[PDB]
Picture (spheres, rainbow over the protein chains, first blue to last red):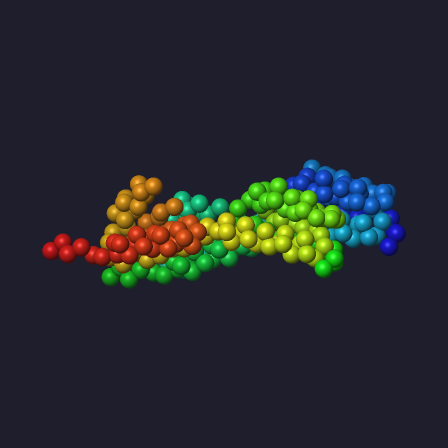
Length: 129
Length: 129
């Protein structure tokens, strides 16, 4: 409740700077005794009573996983990598592998899904004949 | 009704910035206790009583799907891809595939429809003889 402790959550996805008006606004939300502060390493360090920090650290993990963009690298079944590169690149990162033939992709999980749906569009090997 | 809660809808299609006069105008619409705020990740975070947030989050999903432009990639039946490229490009994105022969297209659903109607214009293989 009123218990004043310091507890520290980074925003890894984004530089935490963007919560400085928000979180010292949450200092500015209620009766003070609060500290919000920022390392270059992008950890967000807090001090405050138990509730103000409840919804402060709420803000912080929030802006973390709602600032998500995260890595995945995926196979390419048949089609040559350079191609699916050529298409998706100029559609507006995207990495190709011919040796093991992989499409490699970054973004949020919603980038994961959207470009997995582009993949599912073309995973098919053409019946060139 | 009067229940004050924070609830958060992104505008994925557009950067949510364009609702800052609108939604803090909806703070400014009625008796306050409201917060509207914006992540770089383009999620739009709200705080307010149940009705003001009813029509606030209304605004937000609204400007989402009315800011729609969304992806689809489509086959090309016969005609070479470079061609239908050449025409539609210089008509004022548009991606070609010769290997699997696909016309690839971005836009709203209304871009979907309009250029599906250009497609239906020429899907036909010419009787070159």
